[PDB]
Amino acid sequence: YYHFQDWRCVNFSFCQDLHHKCKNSRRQGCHQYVIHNNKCIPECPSGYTMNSSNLLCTPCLGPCPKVCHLLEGEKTIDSVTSAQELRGCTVINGSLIINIRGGNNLAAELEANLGLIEEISG
Amino acid sequence: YYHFQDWRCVNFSFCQDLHHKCKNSRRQGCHQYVIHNNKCIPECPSGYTMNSSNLLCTPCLGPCPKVCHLLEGEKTIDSVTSAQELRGCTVINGSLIINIRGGNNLAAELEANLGLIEEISG
Image 1 (cartoon, each protein chain N blue to C red):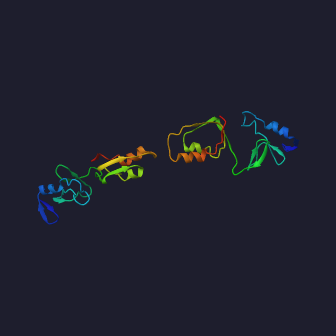
Image 2 (cartoon, each protein chain N blue to C red):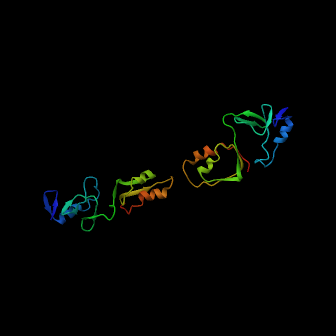
């Protein structure tokens, strides 16, 4: 069993049911529960990321992956400034629209801010 | 008569003959003589420009016109920096090659540096 909500013991399957795919509602209606130090908790602590097949928090290989949840599931990038808002992101939860008409040293600037994105869900 | 070379009196026609169209040789072999304060002199003093039909130096309406003689008779403008080298020019003696691939606020920057050019001899 695992320690839950600082008062009861629950099994893996319970923690797993909570975790599973609260489809949309990221903003107060999901968390996606994880296992860490025999506790079933809302999210991995700092320095940890979630090993997917077993809900288990494991320490990060270098800096932790960073999931960026977009407002309304979308974001339009039309400048270096808007691209910067995604700096450090490795996972985009949503969809991206690229609308860049001008500027300077864009390939390097865009690579600095968007070069770490590994996945886009939309 | 006019005062010439600080020792003799010469007539208008003499000053005019000196002035006339020493075709090329701008760099030590021309000057184009002018009239100022009853002197026939190599060039207009600061604040004056030459009224063309009578060789007479007249005070400048605002800043004075500026002749820019190009090295080898040409110049390639490929940046804001190279354009700046022509800032203030009203006459180009030579030919211009424009090769601008990128940058920012170019229309304003180029107009600031090249917007006063009235004539190109090549």
